Amino acid sequence: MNKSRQKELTRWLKQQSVISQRWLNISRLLGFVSGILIIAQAWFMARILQHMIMENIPREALLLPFTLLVLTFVLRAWVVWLRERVGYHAGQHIRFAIRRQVLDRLQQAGPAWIQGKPAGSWATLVLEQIDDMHDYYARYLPQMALAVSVPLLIVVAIFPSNWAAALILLGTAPLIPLFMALVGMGAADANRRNFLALARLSGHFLDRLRGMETLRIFGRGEAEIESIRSASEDFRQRTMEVLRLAFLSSGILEFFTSLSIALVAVYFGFSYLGELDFGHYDTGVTLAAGFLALILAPEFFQPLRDLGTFYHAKAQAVGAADSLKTFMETPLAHPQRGEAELALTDPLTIEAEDLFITSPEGKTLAGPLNFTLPAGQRAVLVGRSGSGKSSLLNALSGFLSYQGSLRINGIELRDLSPESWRKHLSWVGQNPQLPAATLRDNVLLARPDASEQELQAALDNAWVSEFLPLLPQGVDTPVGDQAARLSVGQAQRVAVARALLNPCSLLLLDQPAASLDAHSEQRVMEALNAASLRQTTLMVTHQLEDLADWDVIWVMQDGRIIEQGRYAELSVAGGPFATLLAHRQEEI
Amino acid sequence: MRALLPYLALYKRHKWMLSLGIVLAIVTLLASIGLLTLSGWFLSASAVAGVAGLYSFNYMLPAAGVRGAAITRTAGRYFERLVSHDATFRVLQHLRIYTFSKLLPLSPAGLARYRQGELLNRVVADVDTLDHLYLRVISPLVGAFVVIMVVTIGLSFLDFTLAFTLGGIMLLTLFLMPPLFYRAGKSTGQNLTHLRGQYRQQLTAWLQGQAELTIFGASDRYRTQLENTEIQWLEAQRRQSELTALSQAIMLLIGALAVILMLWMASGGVGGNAQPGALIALFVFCALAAFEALAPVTGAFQHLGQVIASAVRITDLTDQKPEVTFPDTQTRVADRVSLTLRDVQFTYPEQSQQALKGISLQVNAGEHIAILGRTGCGKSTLLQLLTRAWDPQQGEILLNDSPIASLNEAALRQTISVVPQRVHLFSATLRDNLLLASPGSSDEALSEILRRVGLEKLLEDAGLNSWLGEGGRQLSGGELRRLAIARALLHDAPLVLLDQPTEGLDATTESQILELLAEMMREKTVLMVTHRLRGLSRFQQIIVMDNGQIIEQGTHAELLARQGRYYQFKQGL
Ligand SMILES: Nc1ncnc2c1ncn2[C@@H]1O[C@H](COP(=O)(O)OP(=O)(O)OP(=O)(O)O)[C@@H](O)[C@H]1O
Ligand SMILES: Nc1ncnc2c1ncn2[C@@H]1O[C@H](COP(=O)(O)OP(=O)(O)OP(=O)(O)O)[C@@H](O)[C@H]1O
């Protein structure tokens, strides 16, 4: 974090005050009015005290200023109330807008960029970093002008009685900025380091909490405590490090203010005794001027201390804005966000030539794939594990970045208006998880207004109603955290039922028969064949039985496809496919 | 308010450091009052008889009286906050460990009640709200109390009535305002805590599954509900700000009333003489300056409507009994282990139908058995009962002719290794993600065991210093299974529980893995739960349907002879 980065962050933070300067102006005006009122009160009190003490005049003749003093006090209270309320509202609005922007960008990002940090870090960044700019956006910005304006009025009102006190105050004034600018940068860097440590701690704790079963079965019940202790110590040290600087700045400012007050009081006390007699307009010095200066000087010094206090809030905001600004300037998958709709119906055709699917870091997960699926049909991918089949499916879905291929129906996939494009897909996924709360909502995640086709969907894929009359409630069972209510093999059927509810135009079937016995997998396979016969499909099945009428077989390994044929022509001497089939049939 | 009692007892370890804070607070408050009082009295009394007859000797009031009040006012404050804070965090971190420990020994069905998205909130953001309790709750009250009594006693020497009036007004405000400002703060803080927890849980649940939400177009609804649950949180924050502003206004009005009363009343004489002179100034200035000490009293009590909720949440989290319990000093590890299950009956909590009833089996000195069944038949429940996750409701589960319960955690967790069918990738270095089995090992055996399983592609480029899991490289669906198998051979142990190997691997890789597993495990006992009927040459085959053993054949031959179960399992149906 050098000086240029802080300047850029300050500019970015200042950019967002456009929708609240309207209330910032009102806050500044209210502060100015309060600054006038307090001077009026001080003058009234000084006159009352001088008349009461020197001339021994009874109270009745001074019955007038008491009412004015009371009115001034009431007006001051009302003004401070209004100013506080306006400031808070102006502070809240900008945070609302910033959080909306951040959530919009995060939604636009996708599932590949989201995994760049643990979910705990994302939650901490969304909550704490956004919420920690309220002090900067509410207090410091209006105060930046009040701390300049009010002392000038105070010293101007003090001037027409004795220039010595005004000169003392003016001489004492310039020292404070020189002594806050010496710690501003240290605060601004310590804040960012502290926030990074907190994010690390939160992410570590969440990740450790998610996988407690492995820790229990392996007995690692001692090292995790050590890691948590180290993270806590790292957090505490940074917190203490920033608080120390804050305390030092506050103490220095308090010391200087106290010294100036003492000097002014000493001078005014000595002037009356006839020992100094140098500062006056050749008319002596009266008790009113001394009392006015004594009452007004601490209030002259207060705004500078307030600015010094809010400077560290500004530093906190600057440090917090470092983590969410870098994320907002990282290119997405396709940095255009194109706009086009590929009609409706019109059976699709996926054609790619020399498609090199990359990674969200810069790696390569594929090679020069060359293929074309003609007007429907069904396709199966079979090969050695770790080739890039799931990468191809993800690239087709639109979660990765490709290079110059994979056009459909003559239109490049880069500019298909993602929101419109994702309507033609019925994903099945590998190792599925249930993101809803009730078992009925997961099976209704696509079209949430249906009550008759639900039974047909649950009975067509079959064997999801076999265990229905066994759960406590029924189709409204509150499934566990990830899938704890159900087993592993009973979530695959739920996912299959979810993927078969409504029609589509492209069916990207991942491995559907995972952790299933023979009968259940056979029924699900029959249902999936019936569903898949009606439109374009893409399957990545891993078993080499019952593929005699799948129209095409693409054997792929090392991130490329060698053989693209049919079962009859590939089961005789078809190289790797023959070896795989021989292994499968001999091992049984 | 008994919920705050246990967390207010953490003073026996930092008593002196925290008491020094209150001592310094009263010292600096006294200095702050005295500076203004003495300055005002000097300025007033140097003008009556100061014009002529310089008999009010000068070099005592400014020099000793004021220069000694400009240092203590500052040096007192800086050391006051620097010490206390240092103690407070030194306590909080300790709590952040303690709770975590109480979260460890209940993985199954223990934390299945609480959502995993809000336990993080309780651990992290619900222990950082007690700093208000440890900083602002105690010191300002005692400071204001002592300062008020000291000032009133000092001023009572002249005209009892005035000092008594000032002290009574201050004491009435002190004893009245906090009990009146606790009320709305209670409800507002309760709403704050509940809504913050709910929002964090929902935001965490929105991620971790963005792919399925965005593929099926089900993100707008969840986003709308997120904004809906954030709006009320913002509203409650606004209510809190409004209450704080009203508190400040009331304080200012009370100060104005006190100043006006002390100015007007001190006319007929502050103690005889009917015309005091130079005393009214000090009496006015003391009242003017005394309320800066009492100003922060109500902000400490108003925010007690939020700390109580966090204390209640933490107390609920930390007061849950375990469900297993372990004995002591019974390790006595061995090399050959048998297994006996006479009767096993289990019912999952909150359920009403038995998921596992009537199971009996016996494995003798390093056998090799595999169990088959339907998609749901409680086969993974049987394995998890052997690692003492739940407690059986009937029968016994022997181990080497000895009860399982009479074995400490250092033995049952030592001679047992498992390969679960749901692998987890910790966001840690590959060397730390694989040393769970054997922490000692070496840096050479790791590569050797990683090369035989067949990965051969992770110990490249950076190698064993790469960052896996979230925030780094993410393994595929088969590499995860191979890694799970890999971190089950270093652990060794004379009893292995392979839950489901080779689920997501092709024929060649699965064949290599099977050959490796057969070669390395020869003197051990294997209990496999497989769905592929591949190479079943084991010494015992067992089939389940709902609860019991349909046929315990154990030869793989008479199943081909007797046309019962498993005869139709492999031909087709
Ligand atoms: N983001 C990534 N960064 C680095 N390597 C990656 C990334 N995503 C995938 N890989 C690696 O790519 C290789 C193969 O690609 P991919 O993950 O698509 O395998 P796959 O063909 O789907 O495997 P299988 O289907 O057999 O599980 C693996 O070694 C995997 O770890
Ligand atoms: N956490 C849980 N709470 C209550 N019941 C559960 C829980 N986990 C599983 N069950 C129940 O256990 C029964 C099946 O047992 P289990 O989960 O061991 O199946 P399984 O036969 O091992 O399945 P698979 O072969 O897919 O692993 C079902 O009735 C299921 O609802």
Image (tube, rainbow, N blue to C red):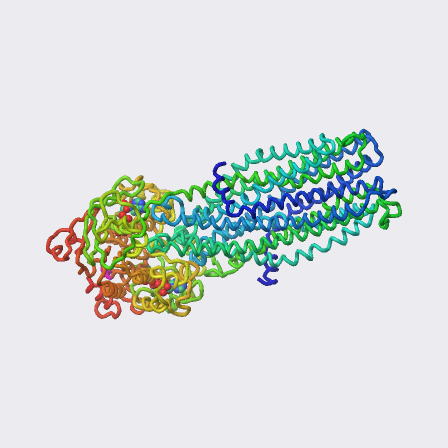
Which residue corresponds to the image point at 53% horizontal and 47% vertical from the top-left?
B14
Picture layout, residue A307 above or below residue A410: above
Picture layout, residue B181 above or below residue A185: above
Which residue corresponds to the image point at 77% horizontal and 48% vertical from the top-left?
A264
Region in magenta: A544-548
Q: What x and y, as percent, mark residue A282?
A: 89, 47
Q: Is residue B573 left or right of residue B317?
A: left
What is the count of numbered marks?
Answer: 0
Q: Is residue A193 left or right of residue A306?
A: left
Q: Is residue A405 left or right of residue A153?
A: left
> Is residue A546 found inside the magenta-colored segment of the image?
yes
Q: What x and y, as percent, mark residue B510?
A: 26, 63
Residue A458 in view here: no
Residue nearest the observer in this picture, B226 or B380:
B380
Q: What x and y, as percent, mark residue B459?
A: 37, 68
Residue nearest the observer in this picture, A329 or B373:
B373
Residue nearest the observer in this picture, B357 or B229:
B357
